[PDB]
Length: 129
Length: 130
Picture 1 (cartoon, each protein chain N blue to C red):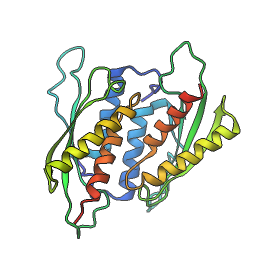
Picture 2: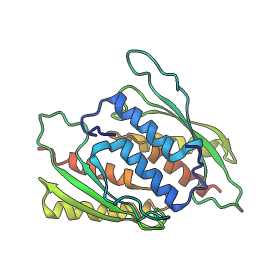
Picture 3: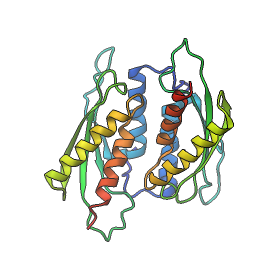
């Protein structure tokens, strides 16, 4: 990696965020468009299986999948956020988390934000564990 | 990467954050540690040359180096944060930014936080574009 961060293009920043998410979450990360092709980069869609922060081996765990699609001008605009496969969470709790995530994303415009969104989910899951 | 995020140890969490910082910031990221010599790695000290985001080239931009050293129990404890090589920022503005990075780091305990610290710096630099 010998590129500079300030002059990057939108496809370069999104591709680099996917590599960062893969290094951080590993098997909990899934690229839903791994065979993306074309002259222009397709909007990436990723799936993050997230767990409560600081979960021990003796604890029962609630979980949820953070599904994010990045528009062409991401991260200058907010991504499409979805919450799927919630375990141990009520429908009102999932709707509450999605509203807080969409509002955190509005204030996080200008830089890649999926990791901070995932951190707030894991913090939310810890409070509901 | 076939690891799981929930069961990682402190050295794994720190090594994965460095790989994420290197992939996102590239040449603006510097690992200030010498070659890994021993069974355990020295605590990571990184340097991030940060600029305001979305630079048009028509604006007068400020910059600063975000220098972070992570303790062994990072990110369960806050890392050591230093702001170096500030260009266009007064020492009061730099010390004001450092105080906010330290309080942001306190609330971000439990998960690696250099990305959110870097974003907070870039947002601070954007407000000084003359």
